[PDB]
Amino acid sequence: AAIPENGNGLDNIDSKSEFAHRIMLTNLLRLLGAVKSKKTTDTRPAQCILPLSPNHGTFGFDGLYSESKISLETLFNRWYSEDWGSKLTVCGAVIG
Amino acid sequence: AALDALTAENKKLAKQQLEVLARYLQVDLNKGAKSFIKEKEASAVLQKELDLWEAEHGEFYAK
């Protein structure tokens, strides 16, 4: 799930950009954290397929899209650092 | 001219009688108005804390 936001630069990070970042990052991690909380067994993991992007700010005015997508790459090492490794498995797909 | 002057004194007598009757019955003739004023300013307080959210976040985020 994503919002189409365009024309939003660094000087025009607006309500749509904040809400899109909320959808794409902070409640995306909340679905994963809630599925982690509703699981009781370490034998049935959920393979989260993360829509990563290969263009982290290399394009122009997209709002917080690059900020939303580069912050999903933290789950690759947060898989090791936290207690949901056997609970969620991260499989980031870099869509071209 | 003078018809309105006498109508005004008739209604003046009616008001002075209504206040005496409301005093006799211990009726707060403005309790509704005072409560409306005190709950309309509470609406102002909640609107002040509500518009903080919309100023801080925006219309799109709020909707």
Image (tube, coloured by chain):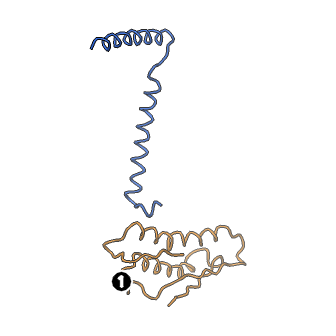
Residue found farthest to the bottom: A96
> Chain letter for orange?
A
Find numbered disc 1 in the image and state the secondary structure of the residue it sits on.
Answer: loop
Pinpoint residue A51: horizontal percent, then vertical percent.
53, 82
Q: Which residue is mark 1?
A: A60
- Which residue occupies 50% across, 91% down? A96
- Which residue occupies 43% across, 12% down? B19
Chain of the residue under the numbered disc 1 shown in the image: A
- Amino acid beneath label 1: Gly
Label 1 Cα crowd, 10 Å radius (few <14 / some 14-19 / many 20+): few
> Residue A64, located in which quarter of the rendered image?
bottom left
Q: Does A4 sit left or right of A84 as displayed? A: left
Q: Quadrant of the N terminus of chain B?
A: top left
Q: Nearer the viewer, residue B7 or A33?
A: B7
> Chain letter for blue?
B
* In this view, B62 is above or below A60: above
Pinpoint residue B47: horizontal percent, then vertical percent.
41, 46
Q: Does A1 sit left or right of B60 as displayed? A: right
Q: Does A45 sit left or right of B63 as displayed? A: right
Q: Nearer the viewer, residue A15 or A94?
A: A15
- Which residue occupies 61% across, 68% down? A34
* In this view, B36 is above or below A17: above
Q: Nearer the viewer, residue A70 or B18?
A: B18
Pinpoint residue A92: horizontal percent, then vertical percent.
55, 85
* In this view, A96 is above or below A63: below
Pinpoint residue B12: horizontal percent, then vertical percent.
36, 11
